[PDB]
Image (tube, grey):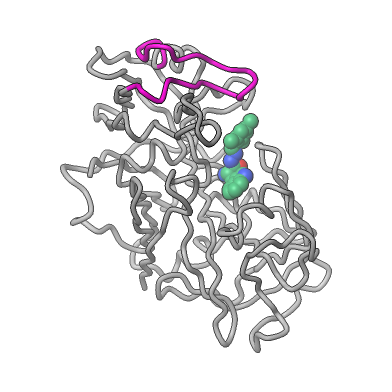
């Protein structure tokens, strides 16, 4: 089997991408944020604290003839940004782009943090990291991909995120028309439950490439590119007037700037992020200070190749017995 679904930016800055997912019978379509940095499929629901719902579409398990309470199961997730959500668990039929999993754990939110409440366009998250991170207790549950994997034509999914445009998540096949040149594959460590890999270095604009190992995670659920402070300082030093602002919470730059590109290494290959991808616009409405799309990972504890990096590539998440990651230009 295979599945193919379009993923759409939630706003004009590509702050996140949402993908329609069918849950239950008859189908209830919710727009979920596919998150390769976590392993829970959780949704706004008829159980979510009313004051914490602000415009989201909700899953109502009582209206689904295939929903079953997973008795005694609860879940609770704390994301590294400080966001959180928790609740109880149903199993139900879940389909993405024509690919159907029966008996998928659907984690129904009773509580969500304010960040989720404020994101009216995000109806929940669909985790695509390794199932070892799933938070369901006392019986850990499998991700949608892990449940689908044996049935898929090939045990893979791909992320093809657009810059200021829709893109595609495919399951079970590699669309050879979706990228240019060849796909370069690189090793993955699953020791922390993430799609963790090591970039071979970086360049800023037309500058020379610096060969240096940068360990980090491929995370479709994170907006920006978070890298070591040394690398990030080298990037912003090429933008007149750029500075790190503790009051704003990262690097800002004059909105009048033309940003340089940023290149990252994948083995001997190179992925170029155009300068425009690194512009996140005014820090507040009408400001001439703009927020940067490359930020320091210092204090996060891990480097994060978020959407700013991933949207510059066609990315293969290879879930074979020994997982690997592939990157191609597009
Ligand atoms: C200090 C710091 C700052 C950020 C932005 C992150 C990213 N975290 N990103 C994630 O955890 C995502 N994989 C999922 C996620 C967290 N909060 C969200 C809000 C909306 C949509 C997705 C997420 C971290 C780990 C630490």
- The number of discs equals 0
Is the residue 273 above or below the residue 229 in the image?
below
In the rendered image, the residue lying farthest to the left is 181
Residue 232 drawn above or below residue 32: above
The answer to whether residue 74 of the structure is visible from this angle is: no
Looking at the picture, tell me which residue is in the foreground, 173 or 246: 246
Front residue of this view, candidates 308 and 270: 308
Is residue 122 rendered to the left or right of residue 265?
Answer: right
Tell me which corner region of the image, top left, top right, bottom left or bottom right, holds residue 137: bottom right
The reply to whether residue 156 is visible in this rendering is yes
Q: Nearer the viewer, residue 145 or 162?
A: 162
Is residue 239 found inside the magenta-colored segment of the image? Answer: yes
10 shown above or below 282: below
* Extent of the magenta region: 236-257
| Residue 285 is covered by the magenta coloring | no
Quarter of the image that includes the N terminus: bottom left
| Frontmost residue, 70 versus 110 | 110
| Residue 191 on image: x %, y % | 57, 37
- Residue 6 at x, y percent in the picture: 37, 63
Splitting the image into 4 quarters, where does residue 245 fall? top right
Task: Return the x and y of residue 33 as percentages of the image width and height.
Answer: 53, 56
């Amino acid at each position: 089997s295979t599945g193919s679904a379009t993923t759409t930016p939630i706003d004009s800055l590509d702050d996140a991408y949402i993908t329609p997912v069918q849950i239950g019978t008859p189908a209830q379509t919710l727009n979920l944020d596919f998150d390769t940095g976590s392993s829970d499929l959780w949704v706004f629901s008829s159980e979510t604290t009313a004051s914490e719902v602000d415009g989201q579409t909700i899953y109502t398990p009582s209206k689904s003839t295939t929903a079953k309470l997973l008795s005694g199961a609860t879940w609770s997730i704390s994301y590294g940004d400080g966001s959180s959500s928790s609740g109880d668990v149903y199993t139900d039929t879940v389909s993405v782009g024509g690919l159907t999993v029966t008996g998928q754990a659907v984690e129904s939110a009773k509580k969500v943090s304010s960040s989720f409440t404020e994101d009216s366009t995000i109806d929940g998250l669909l985790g695509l990291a390794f199932s070892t991170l799933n938070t369901v207790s006392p019986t850990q549950q499998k991700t949608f991909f892990d449940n689908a994997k044996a049935s898929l034509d090939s045990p893979v999914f791909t992320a093809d995120l657009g810059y200021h445009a829709p893109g595609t998540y495919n399951f079970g096949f590699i669309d050879t028309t979706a990228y240019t040149g060849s796909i370069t594959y690189t090793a993955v460590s699953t020791k922390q439950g993430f799609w963790e890999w090591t970039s071979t270095g970086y360049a800023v604009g037309s500058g020379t490439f610096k060969s240096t190992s940068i360990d980090g995670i491929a995370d479709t659920g994170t907006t920006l590119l978070y890298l070591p402070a040394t690398v990030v300082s080298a990037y912003w030093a090429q933008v007149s007037g750029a500075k790190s602002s503790s009051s704003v919470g990262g690097y800002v730059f004059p909105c009048s700037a033309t940003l340089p590109s940023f290149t990252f290494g994948v083995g001997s290959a190179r992925i170029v992020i155009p300068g425009d991808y690194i512009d996140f616009g005014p820090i507040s409405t009408g400001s001439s200070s703009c927020f940067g799309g490359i930020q320091s990972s210092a204090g996060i504890g891990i480097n994060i190749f978020g959407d700013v990096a991933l949207k510059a590539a066609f990315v293969v998440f290879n879930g074979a017995t020994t997982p690997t990651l592939g990157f191609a230009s597009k």
